Amino acid sequence: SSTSLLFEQLNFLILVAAEAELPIAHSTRKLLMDNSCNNCQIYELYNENLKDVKTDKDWFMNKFGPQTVHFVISNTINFPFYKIVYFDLLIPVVSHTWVQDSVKTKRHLRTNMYSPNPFHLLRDCQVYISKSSFNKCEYILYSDLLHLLGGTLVNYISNRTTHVIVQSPQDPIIATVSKLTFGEKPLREWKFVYPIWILYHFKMAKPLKGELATLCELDMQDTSEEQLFAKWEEVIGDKQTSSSQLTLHPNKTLFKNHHFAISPDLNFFTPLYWFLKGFIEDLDGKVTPLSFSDDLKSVYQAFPDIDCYIGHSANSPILEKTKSIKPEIHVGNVSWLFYMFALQKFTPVSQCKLIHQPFHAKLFTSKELTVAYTNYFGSQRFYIQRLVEILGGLSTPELTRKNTHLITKSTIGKKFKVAKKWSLDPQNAIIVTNHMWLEQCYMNNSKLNPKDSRFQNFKLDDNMGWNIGQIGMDH
Amino acid sequence: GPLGSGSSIRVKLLQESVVKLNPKLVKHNFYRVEANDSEEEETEFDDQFCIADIQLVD
Picture 1 (tube, rainbow over the protein chains, first blue to last red):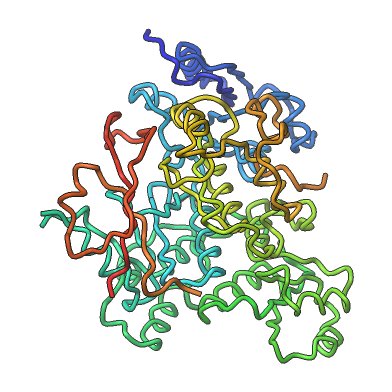
Picture 2: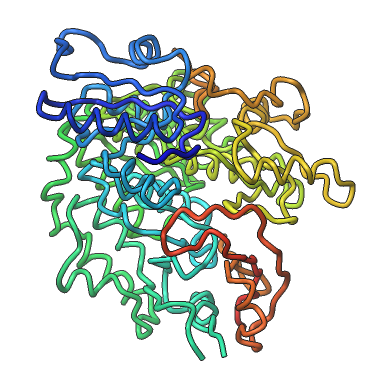
């Protein structure tokens, strides 16, 4: 067998679901070891009586740490710590073929296509969401659902972009992307779709096909609001009940005895509000939209069951007034709802992540904070994109001289080597720092010094608790 | 809310391709990509890319 440094400094956990799977686990461990993995654990699910022990984050960190686990190798998601591994710790879960194909092709293949989660219906998609179609709260919601469906969000157009999400034929991005020609050969064949392409997969938990697939395609004749409304109603309207969305997410009373007040600073396209309201009510929750003209004391007196506030911005005066009337109210954003849906448990915001509270005012500008990142995998990449976005900056998967920072947790790879040299060049002077700088800047709402020693620690993978997304969580 | 006139989008292009790009598109900037990591068989290990900021067409 051949050897390489492909998996240098990475830790793997192989979950064996049945005795017959042991030879596959052995061959995968050999592949990992021959290509220089740091550590490879094999864990036989069938050989412990796990149905009487809480397999929570503490259990997982104690059993498989103290170092982090970079990848879980499993051909199934049917193990009782899947949600804490995947949705909390943000560790990818991939089939054995991810290892086999990554060795064959001598590279770290994207993990999405190898997820064994049947709800990851968009796993093969690389999706660009147009910022000239959507406001910030719409963009964040569509990004959240795309991510929950296993797709990849991109903020650049390339010949690998599979879908471009647009609101209407009036978006100028349509003609711009269509003019990306060379001579006149196109960069690729483009698929422009309305956001109901995402929403249908999320609501129905099955692939789009037939006429409903065609209705999600951009139609340049849809020049009126009425025509857009009509397509939304046919594709995700009340006659399309969630046929198998609850098969994969069986807690139909997730939001029972909760009643959410929806802040007016969420200015959704109205059929998108209807989608969100229906999503909550389908989980036995209640919904009351607030208006800028409401007398809040009157509203909360009439609906004393309202116990949650959902809003976009931390600095909304509506939220300030709400907290003075209801001091114990849960204060979250829309992302928080979808995180509880993923966890299948109602969870107070203080036990969730930094990205699940109404967002701070932008701390940085894009001129100050345009960051490349490296050595993150899977949902960690989505998290850093979101964190940089709500700090006020821009993120890039590529490294260029436009970048102000490189964010990394280790010293491996080409970008770290290049950026370290650039940091010493006065003509460039990029800053290399770890993700805890981003997290602490946001949590403290303050521009911390990225060269502090705690942000120059590039051995964070030595402790699983330093995984990105852990800062800010209450036990 | 949404970005409007005069804004741009990011386009990742082979460096070779830039000189052949539609001359009617307005390029705000172009940046050479360094330390590219191919994560798909469709990208070759030594492909040289750039990022172009392309103005939205009027």
